Length: 407
Image (cartoon, rainbow, N blue to C red; front, side, top):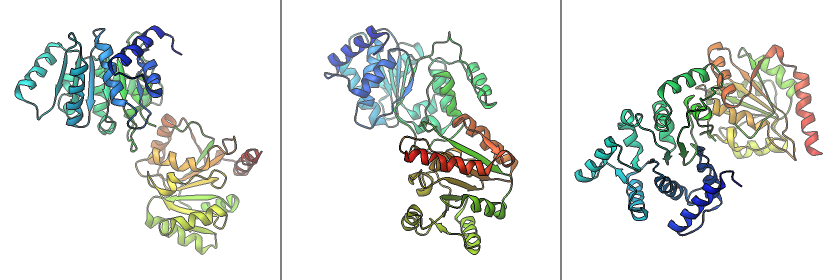
């Protein structure tokens, strides 16, 4: 249901009349948001009417004299949307588009009204945004629809451009980021009333600190942290293979070791094999070493830190994977790789979010401190020092949480 229902049914009707069919499940949901002036990420598959909704919404906003911008990754998408719009458009609505392979006549029409603010709907690509950041940031759109997600996150300058495009002053963006950098949360001014920002998808390769400005300014998150987690993060201020040996001696079983490089991984594999530990590697034979580890044949599994890796993301065994050890912090620092990797030790099993332990071996105070603040902003989780870690109690929490799971 929706408070502001009257605007929802007014949207619902207009859609069915113009488009011809009724809003779909996702579209209804999205509809109830747009009606309330909430921005959001379109978490849905392809072919369920993502572009159609953005298009129809812009049309519905034009009736009330509100302006929209529709940003696409390709030119053909710009054309196709322009064509569809001008066919569905009424007599009043002013619609203009722009791409490089456009006629000089049609180009000047766009540039004329663009400067004169004589438009209701604008359609251009992500390239256009890169060429016209200055001019764009000087305009406020009630609705901005971004189809390409990576483009938004490729340059920190991009995020700022959209933000200002939705009526968020540059001064407020600086103060917001200045606040977020310190690790605090920024309380946007309640009298600002920004426009609607809608991002079509979520990047399979997110990067940066910038993407957090949507969280405090438009109250939505571009990135895809996990629903929830129960992980204890502990840091070891060195690379002591023997500080490691005495950890494996109490952990004993269900251990994953992520090395920065395949070279350092082999070195670590040699050392542990030399001390007669039951260890296996994943760079040579993954399918077989993981199944042995899965069945209990192998106690320790060593791998290589990679964003979309087999061991970092793919593996799904909360009942088997209890402890995650990082031989050096993922290069970057790569909080998203650390996040995915440490999540192997903690997820829902038979109605219990089991307890997981993540240990980081980092000697570089500088690199570790970066990882710490970033983990705090993204996953709202902290990393404790070895001296605050009660290993016996941690091992207990790991075993006890997997009994309450069997219940």
